[PDB]
Image 1 (spheres, rainbow over the protein chains, first blue to last red):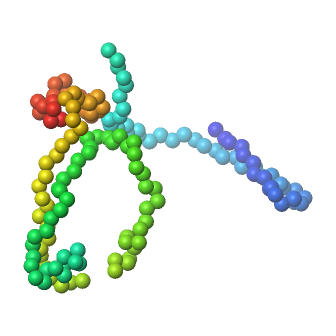
Image 2 (image 1 turned 90 degrees about the horizontal axis):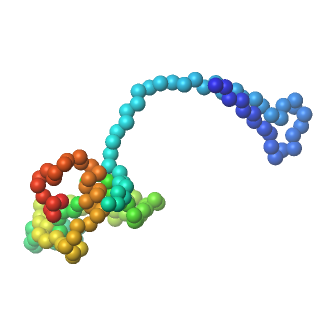
Image 3 (image 1 turned 90 degrees about the vertical axis):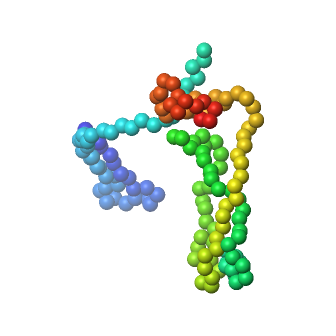
Length: 49
Length: 49
Length: 49
């Protein structure tokens, strides 16, 4: 999936360079590395009888 | 320390105060109290004099 | 700094004591269950735990 972003020039009252804003397209492909889940003790529920 | 070091001139090997052991843990702590994010004192610096 | 050698301190022995009531606390028991998965209590001790 591609991601179109664009930059701007601000605060300085801009001249006519032919470019105030830019354009950046970021390509991102998914990668897979092994998962390793671990279990440790946490807070418990009420469980009222 | 250095006071007891200078006390070594006359007698030696009899001093004691403040118990031995401590415990608190078996997996996780409750943590409903003190923090100290910023910590620095003169002693830690290279000024042991 | 370097003057005399050895000496040091033998820490004094003292007893330990608690909040005074017969019944067991809910937290310490419920939180003891979070770590282990034993059916009955290994060691065979309830109060000392």
